[PDB]
Amino acid sequence: SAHKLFIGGLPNYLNDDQVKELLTSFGPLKAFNLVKDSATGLSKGYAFCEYVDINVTDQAIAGLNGMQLGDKKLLVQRAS
């Protein structure tokens, strides 16, 4: 859907609350998950989210795509 994003490249030590805080700085979320290895529990650095508002979605992909977080760079797209 047009409100949904697929994010990769997050530093693997960031937790759900920290990733969620970065995302909600753009506007409110209606869904979120941070992808984890089922056996180790460690983050894979991917996240999926859905914003309430389409305009926020558009600004979030523009703002997050290419964002540098230390030695990592986010790659973000709409979740077609």
Image (cartoon, helix red, strand yellow):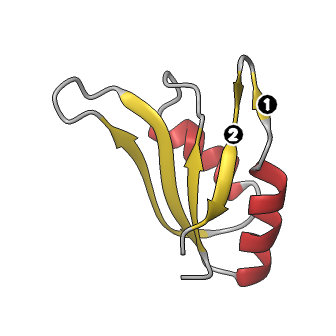
Q: Which residue is mark 2?
A: 74
Front residue (pair 76, 35): 76
Residue found 26% across the figure and 29% down from its top = 41
Relative to residue 34, is residue 42 depicted above or below? above
Q: Is residue 35 left or right of residue 48?
A: left
Q: Secondary structure at mark 1?
A: strand
Q: Is residue 74 left or right of residue 80?
A: right
Q: Which residue is mark 1?
A: 68
Q: Residue furthest left?
A: 39
Calculate the distance from the C-alpha at mark 1 to the C-alpha at mark 2. 7 Å
Question: Looking at the image, which is closer to me, 2 or 20?
Answer: 2
At which x and y percent is residue 33? 42, 53
Residue 38 shown left or right of residue 73 in the figure: left
Q: Are marks 1 and 2 in contact (CB under 8 Å)?
A: yes
Q: Amino acid at mark 2?
A: Leu
Residue 43 figure quarter: top left
Tag 1: residue type? Answer: Gln
In the rendered image, which quarter contains the C terminus?
bottom right
Provide residue 17's location: percent of width, then percent of height. 51, 41
The residue that appears at 61% across and 78% down in the rendered structure is 3
Where residue 65 appears, as percent x and y from the top left, is 76, 49
Horizontal side of residue 41 vs 70, given as left or right: left
Total numbered badges shown on the rendered structure: 2
Give the answer, above or below, for where 22 lies relative to 60: above
- Which structural element holds mark 2? loop
Q: Residue at x 79, y 30 (%)?
A: 68
Within 10 Å of disc 2 (Cα), the crowding (few <14, some 14-19, many 20+) is some
Q: Position of residue 4 (x, y in %)?
A: 56, 71
Tell me if mark 1 has few (under 14), some (14-19) or many (20+) residues whose alpha carbon lies within 10 angstroms of its own.
Answer: few
Between disc 1 and disc 2, whose residue precedes? Answer: 1
Q: In which quarter of the view is residue 8 placed? A: top right
